[PDB]
View 1 (cartoon, helix red, strand yellow):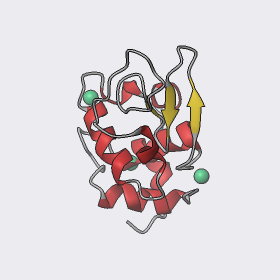
View 2 (tube, protein in one colour):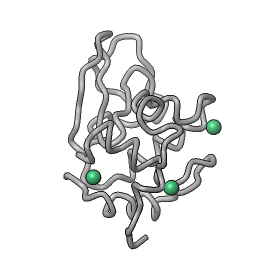
View 3 (cartoon, helix red, strand yellow):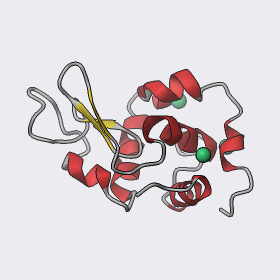
Length: 129
Ligand SMILES: [Cl-]
Ligand SMILES: [Cl-]
Ligand SMILES: [Cl-]
């Protein structure tokens, strides 16, 4: 599923991400934009052989199992394929664990490089939330 911007903002809001660990909703929408272009089916292979999955490009190196990332962990206790669903529940629940891990949203390289410190409120402008 390719979410509309406000569609995803509303989905993220109802799933409890607005100000989760102090990150306003626009931060999450911005991260999703640059990680996946709002596409739940986004996947990308990393140089180390792990793969990023879904709307927030969650990495099999640590967070999910895909059976093809040797020596990795599965800290969200989920198949990586669950992170590709049209329903963002699994991705959101796992994201909550990731952002609580120590470095906050810096865990998402695209957030650090493209969202952090910017006017992220613009990402939820005009949205019915
Ligand atoms: Cl957009
Ligand atoms: Cl915001
Ligand atoms: Cl933080």
